[PDB]
Amino acid sequence: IPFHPYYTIKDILGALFMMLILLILVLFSPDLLGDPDNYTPANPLNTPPHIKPE
Amino acid sequence: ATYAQALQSVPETQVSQLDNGLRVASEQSSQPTCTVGVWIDAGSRYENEKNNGAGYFVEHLAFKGTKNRPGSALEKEVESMGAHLNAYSTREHTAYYIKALSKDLPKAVELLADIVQNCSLEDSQIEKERDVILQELQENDSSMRDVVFDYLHATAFQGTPLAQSVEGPSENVRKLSRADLTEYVSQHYKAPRMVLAAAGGVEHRQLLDLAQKHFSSLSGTYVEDAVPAFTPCRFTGSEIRHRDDALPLAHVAIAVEGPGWANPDNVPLQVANAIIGHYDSTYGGGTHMSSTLASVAATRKLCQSFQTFNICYAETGLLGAHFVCDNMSIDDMMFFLQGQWMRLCTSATESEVVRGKNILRNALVSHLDGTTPVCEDIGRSLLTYGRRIPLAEWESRIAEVDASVVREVCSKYFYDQCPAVAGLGPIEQLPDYNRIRSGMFWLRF
């Protein structure tokens, strides 16, 4: 089927859902997916209790 | 003698009406020949699903036999004076006309009365006639133009009787009976919907007095009470695609809901249609034709037979184009043809409107040449309009339409209206209906 009248609009809808998820994450819990320990300035003398990556 | 004076001459279409309802209408100028025929108002529009195709069968059996003329004896008479009897059955009108010498006018009207009133409808001829129609149905199946227009009517006027084909589905023709045909004749071949017509060496008094003493037996009442009424039809903008890659070319027809017979918008729209014009690969005009779409097509060898149409029924019609091109041109043509319509809806120029008016004038005048086209015009006009439109009135209407009128009427009928596309054959580049409806409006405007 031609791409233009179709999925382009469906792709836009998917992008809107993606924006919904992203905006919820940013605007209601920015640091939900992120360790708070990063907010301490990097000190090469103290090993953090956990060294988990992203 | 300029154009206007010749238009004024225009021998008149004197019309009368005998008591039973039949209205005679003649046009005598000088000619020793004549074309006398009746124009019963019937067709696929006045036909339900159960009996769809009865009218074609009746027209088939009309000339076969009569109570008065037993069998092929009618043919013997008709060929005795060299007359060329013929009949055509559209979706709305079914007509019988005899092309014969004027001196043999008294016999011709008698022959018409026998065919249209005292028809035997004999069973054995029905059985033999059944095979002819079935074979005719296959022939029309190969008629790669006709099936496209049938698809157009089916996919545009869905549900309504207009979608029904003229010949009928190849199952009613195999289950019809004398009973069904006799009801069709009784319920449709009635005097009020009958226009006796003649043109040539036919005195109007002659036609009147012959009609009184031949056609007065026609009745006006309708059985118990049943009167087949008018069922208005609806234009359902849709798409039908019969993809058949074996076919060499790809007939495509696109139309929108155009006006009815009475609507004056026919006169401007036709001019607009004449703007797009028609083209065939054997034309010879080439890349010099004034019609932009024709020039493009001839330059790039896009189509082979594109041509516009203005099929117009009583209350609604189809207005659009039908183009025949190879597989890898449709996507381009739906761009150009639509691209032309929007131009007419936005930037029609009086320079081309004058050309369209001239083309329409020439078409109207040339079409009304010869006795048979004149008789066809009379029979069709007394039904569709109720009066034969004189060429002077056509000239006046053509003079009224100008660039602004054409733009307005095209915007009112073409712009943003859902089409009724219908494909056939190797149609694959044919843009999806979403694309076609997308082309129906111009983002610049």
Image: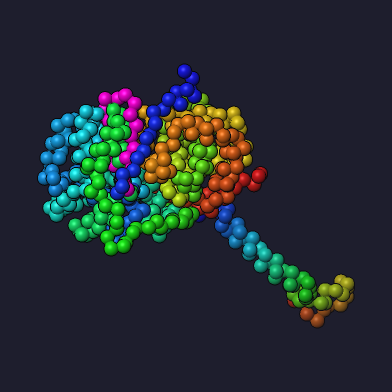
Residue B442's x, y, as percent? 62, 45
Of residue B152 and residue B60, the one placed in the foreground of this image is: B60
Residue range highlighted in magenta: B21-38
Residue at the top extreme of this rendering: B1
Question: Vertically, is A30 above or below B108?
Answer: below
* Residue at the image point whose x is 19% and y is 44% from the top: B114
The reply, left or right, for residue B87 in relation to residue A15 is: left
Residue B220 seen in the figure: yes
The reply, left or right, for residue B368 in relation to residue B201 is: right
Residue B234 belongs to magenta span: no
Residue B176's x, y, as percent? 22, 58
Question: Vertically, is A9 above or below B323?
Answer: below
The reply, left or right, for residue B82 in relation to residue B365 is: left
The reply, left or right, for residue B138 in relation to residue B346 is: left
Secondary structure mostly seen in magenta is: strand
Residue B131's x, y, as percent? 18, 50
Of residue B267 and residue B194, the one placed in the foreground of this image is: B194
Residue B339 seen in the figure: no
Q: Quadrant of residue B160?
A: bottom left
Of residue B264 and residue B235, the one placed in the foreground of this image is: B264
